[PDB]
Amino acid sequence: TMMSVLANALRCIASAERRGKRQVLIRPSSKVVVKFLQVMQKHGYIGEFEIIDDHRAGKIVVNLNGRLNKCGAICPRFDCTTPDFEKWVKNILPSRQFGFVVLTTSLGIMDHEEARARNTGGKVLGFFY
Amino acid sequence: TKKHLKRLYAPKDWMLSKLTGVFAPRPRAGPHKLRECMTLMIIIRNRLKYALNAAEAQMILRQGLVCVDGKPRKDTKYPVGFMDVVEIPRTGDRFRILYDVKGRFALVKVGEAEGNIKLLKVENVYTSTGRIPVAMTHDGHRIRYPDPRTHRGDTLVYNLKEKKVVDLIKSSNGKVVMVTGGANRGRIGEIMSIERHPGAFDIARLKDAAGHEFATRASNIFVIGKDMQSVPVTLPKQQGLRINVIQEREEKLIAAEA
Amino acid sequence: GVVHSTKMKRSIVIRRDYLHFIRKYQRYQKRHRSLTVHCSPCFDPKPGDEVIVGQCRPLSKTIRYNVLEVV
Amino acid sequence: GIVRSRLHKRKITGGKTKIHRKRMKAELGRLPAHTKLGARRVSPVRARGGNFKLRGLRLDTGNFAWSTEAIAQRARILDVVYNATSNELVRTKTLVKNCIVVVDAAPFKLWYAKHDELKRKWMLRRENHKIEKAVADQLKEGRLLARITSRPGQTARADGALLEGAELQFYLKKL
Amino acid sequence: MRNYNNFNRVWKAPRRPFEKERLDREMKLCGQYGLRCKREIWRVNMTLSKMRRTARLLLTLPENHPRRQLEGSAIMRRCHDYGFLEEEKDKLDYVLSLTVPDILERRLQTVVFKHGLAKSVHHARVLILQRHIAVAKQIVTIPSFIVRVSSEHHIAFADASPFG
Amino acid sequence: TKANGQHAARKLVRLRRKNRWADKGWKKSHTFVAQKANPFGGSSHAKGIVLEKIGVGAKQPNSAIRKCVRVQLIKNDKKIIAFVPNDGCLHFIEENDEVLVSGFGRSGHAVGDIPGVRFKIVKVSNVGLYALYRQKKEKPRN
RNA sequence: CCAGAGGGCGCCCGUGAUUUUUUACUGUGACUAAAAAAGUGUGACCAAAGCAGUCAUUCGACUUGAAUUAGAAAGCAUGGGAU
RNA sequence: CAUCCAAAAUCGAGUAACAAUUGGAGGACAAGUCUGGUGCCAGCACCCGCGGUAAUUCCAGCUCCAAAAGCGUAUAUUAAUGC
RNA sequence: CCGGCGUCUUUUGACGAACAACUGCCCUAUCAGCCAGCGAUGGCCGUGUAGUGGACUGCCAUGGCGUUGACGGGAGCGGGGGAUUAGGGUUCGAUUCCGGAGAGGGAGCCUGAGAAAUAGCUACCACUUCUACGGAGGGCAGCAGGCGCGCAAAUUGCCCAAUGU
């Protein structure tokens, strides 16, 4: 089976992006997968997306503008902290300039940049370039 | 039974050095605990400088020229903790030890009639034989016949001119209060609230003047007065307010340009 | 802690379970303290129930605890 | 010497402790004192507190108390009827706490008759008072059953309380 | 026993000492500035690496962090002193543009020569060690004494000097 | 591969503890059979009493004769071979003279063109043998 | 030296819950020997170092300085409520 | 250690004999198109390899190189190791 | 007439002593079962101790621990900390400070507030020194120093001036 929802979604996006395809299908939907997409659509990396309803589990559909290069998943959801933002941001990303790690917090779902700003660490979620 | 102490294992609030000597004095047991006290010899020698050597401190004290609590002492080693008045009548000076801001022993200089005042925190109350009530203090003093309103952790104003206890002061409500130990030493503020955790340490939250709240243990509360304009005793060099690291460094430079 | 067994007269067996952390692998492990307690004849909790236990003076060789309450 | 320690004993896992330390004088048993009947003999020992404790040997007298009326008088210890711990003890008439015993009973009798100015005090005390039946029968004869509620082996004084109905009825039936 | 005085190394040898690239850039210094041996070139390297480590670590941090604030001003302050950097510098990237020569340049040996009080660096190393130089009024007979930006304009000569 | 679970820890630990026994760079440290085997006891040097001078051949690609010394060890009563590592200093070693013995280079493999010998003779009678070779000191027979 | 009115906090105890409620994680705060390390000040001639000293100018001044940070788990308090 | 060679009065370098050494120069690895001696011998060589009379590696001299009042050698341990 | 010392007993702060527990700790399964006659786990009543307690006697019950590695074996005084590493880590800790233990090997004991003390005592064992041989002693892992040992490590010096007791 699949033991991470995110992993199932963002291996469709990455593959599709490397083939230059301008839409992708996503088999499941979660409250979580939504939030992840939302982020990247603000910062300009996605055109739009639709959630469709089968009344069992939804099928997300996304429009890629080709502005992504990867969307990963950090699977164990390891604990990152106020000092350790530095660590992750160096090690898994090609840059500090345009690398975006996305984290979970009690507050919501947000970029590392906004995480530091509000001074709360948390468990990591995923990342994109 | 320990009868030796090494300089490193001794407090560095006595401000000994790593080099020069190997031992430090272990004082005779008395009112105050080993960590919170400062031994006579340390004071006279390293601070006041009426002695340049150990032997010179014996010369002064054994003879007697020095009083604490207004009693003359022939003791070479004796504790001096907190709220103790020491008087050398030869100089004619009256020191009152306290906790200075930044964890330092303060030596503060007082008018002569203030040096008959003293403040002792109560630890336990209990009834002893004959139904005679007793407040036992943090300096080990026994106050016979305390007021019926006395409670644990309150202060008793204590006349050293002749021994008795005038009106008390409670730890109740917001009152001007200062900290003992815990590395918030000498910092003064109002009690904002007193938290309770039964079966465990009772947190209290203090708020010093110009805001900046903080938390310290109930055990480390020592009352001063009713209000900051009703204080019975003097404050050390700084008023009980700490400042940021940046501002320390800034001011150090500004004065060094003179 | 829970109830591991109800065996013995006025003595129960409690099992605490917690998590230790290892830095190198960045991953937790499960480790349990199997402990003995003196259960008051007031209470008699079933296996799997959760118990609360306090700190009392020694009462046997192994027993240091006592049962305050039961859930 | 004799010691009180968990470090010559098996663990809960069935394993064995291993030593690295020679035994302290802090931990320290001593041989049991044997209090019996006969002439009083008291041999002190010095203890760790800087004070003495007294080894009762052969105490034949005790300070006994009657429950409910808040009194007491001395009387003579005659016999031991019973004990929880062993039968062996009882036969040698050793005195150790929570042995049932037998006493002279004479002063209690004397007292209870005192329980013109005097005379009306009696009538007031007779009123709103009663006594168990099994008590009074024995107290008439001049023997009684009591318990020794002080440990005589470390004080060299044997004090006891006198049995009253609830508990008396139990020890009686065990005989 | 009972010694509580520290020891530390101030100099270390770079890895792979037979690099012909490194050899060039060693001799170039040690001959020019009149240095005794390579040990000196390394001594400054260490202390520079040290400084550059904390500066890197500070630079990483978000704005308005206590480490950044306090310790940033200090690093900058002490490069204003000794004249390594000027007072138009503040970034903590300027600090990372410091290299080995700018240190050596402010050693007493070179400063003496450059101020016009000797005819060579070799000659100025003698002038130091023959006890005939000063750094304001204080006789200094160490060539590795780093000279303040203020006090390189008050060098003069010793008052023990037959040349002064 | 590996396990990425949160509570996966103990499986990881036990895996490493197994697979380090397939390393010989683990065994060489932790195991005391290695220590025992080494003729010095794992000490830096040892002394021995010279027994006999033994002429030793050489391997096929480089034909030479090599001068070696059969020595006995005071410490453990083991015998060993060692090489004389200077030109024409076989003289300066004589029978029943105390002598020191060292390892040479790689100490798990024998040196080229001398099989079985990892051992070179540094000092004869605590005198530096190099010192005798390139003359400074003279050998005592005192 | 206010009858009545609802009261409003503080304190202690008693009673009531259809099923009270916790923990990891995180932010902040408590509580925690020195030596050692990171670090602030300072021309021990520099330097490893040290916690000293420095200034007028005398029959002392600086309210002289001797900052500050980190220091595994585990335990403590209190916010947050996504996973 | 420091301060000094008179304050009236007190020493002293020119081969500056007050004279720097320990390991290297085929490759790895900074430095010999050298000269004599030896000739698969003697020996060198961590490893690759040198020596059978034509030796850039041996045994000597000169020359140059690296570090320097320190420099080689042995063993263990750490980095090198994502072996 | 007053002052300064000194002491009995009682009282409780301090300086410490003695117990207990929450959490953590190298390798090994070609060490998987361990524990109860003579205490293993618990209950009940006593005994003992300064005190709690299977610490111990008597009686009664049949439990306790284990692949989340018990039990056994090997290596090792523990920690603060050292070395090395960009990071993660890797490795060391006999040794100045703190804690524990020991004084040739073992056991027993007195005195004292505190000791199972060892430049205190008693005994045995392994050594070892004197004796007109009837007896009497010795314990450096305190400082120097000597012998032995091994690759390997200082003067039978001066001083209580300093730092402490």
Image (tube, coloured by chain):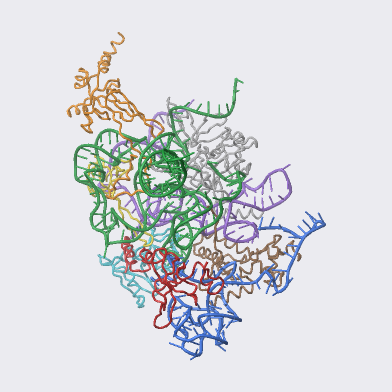
Chain colours: A cyan, C yellow, D orange, E brown, F red, G purple, H blue, I green
Is G9 left or right of C54, judged from the image as shown? right
State the residue at coordinates (67%, 71%): E122
> Residue B160 in the image: x percent, y percent?
56, 31
Residue situated furthest top in the rendering: D116
Q: Quadrant of residue D36?
A: top left
Q: Quadrant of the C terminus of chain B?
A: bottom right
- Does the image show residue F60? yes
Residue B102 vs A69, above or below: the answer is above
- Number of marks in picture: 0
Q: Nearer the viewer, residue I133 or D35?
A: I133
Residue I160 vs B71, above or below: the answer is below
> Residue I70 in the image: x percent, y percent?
28, 53
> Residue A51 in the image: x percent, y percent?
31, 68
> Residue G23 in the image: x percent, y percent?
34, 52
- Does the image show residue E18? no
Q: Nearer the viewer, residue G56 or I78?
A: I78
Q: Nearer the viewer, residue A49 or B252?
A: B252
Residue B132 vs A97, above or below: the answer is above
